[PDB]
Amino acid sequence: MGIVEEAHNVKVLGTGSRFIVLAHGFGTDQSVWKHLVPHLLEEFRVILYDNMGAGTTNPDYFDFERYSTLEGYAYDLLAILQELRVDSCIFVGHSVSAMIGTVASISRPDLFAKIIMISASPRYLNDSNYFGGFEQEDLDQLFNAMASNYKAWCSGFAPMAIGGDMESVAVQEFSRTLFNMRPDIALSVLQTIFKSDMRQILCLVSVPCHIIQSMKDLAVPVVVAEYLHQHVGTESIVEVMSTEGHLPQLSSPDVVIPVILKHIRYDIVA
Ligand SMILES: CC1=C[C@@H](O)OC1=O
Image (cartoon, rainbow, N blue to C red; front, side, top):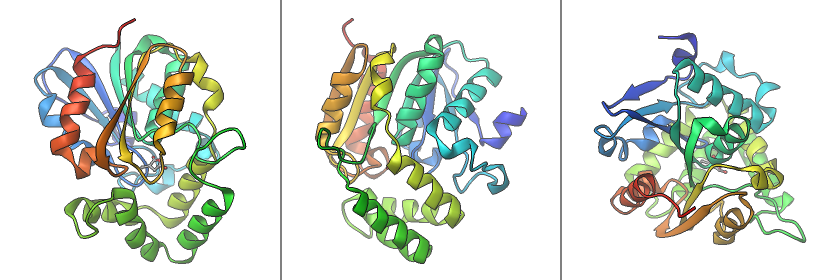
């Protein structure tokens, strides 16, 4: 394996000709895609990778300056796509990875045939002019909790992010990946995500975007999906699903997998 492949736990599965890249969100890893991957093996070559800072990655590679902005993660994605020699791909970014691929696509639009966003937001904090879902006090509270008892925070956060029954399998799975992060990395990364503001780069997007989210998502009001639709600088489409949860591809795969497959297969009218 190449040096980049190894560092990000890169996997390339399936026997298709076209590439599809699945990029996971905060607190989880490439296993979040477990219900989707079996349906792509015949049509594509599926690229899975882990973000630096996930519990599956080496904590000594986490460079706090590099990842102080989402650009740092976008550089990692480009490096992965280069090492693998992708010509073009369909990119599926979950949570923060939606914006990471968006940033990457502005530097290299040739690499991206289409972006599919799941549980995406360009900004979580409110503005007298924009509703992201959170005030600064909400954040201060979250971070005080994380810093004071990470193990306890993971147990209470997991059911909230996942939604539905608090003793479900998906909650256990997310709870476990959450606690596998080094607490100071988890704290730093979630702060970086919650403070971010990508609104101004949306009009520069030149790759069509499919914007998918649960109707009940603790971190993404439904109006943020409309916001991304309005401000993305090219063709885009919204699909709000009748599901609850920030990781719906994991907690409601029976419902969510067909939606993602639909947006992989069909294209938006130019
Ligand atoms: C999983 C997730 C949390 C959200 O705030 O952004 C993400 O990446």
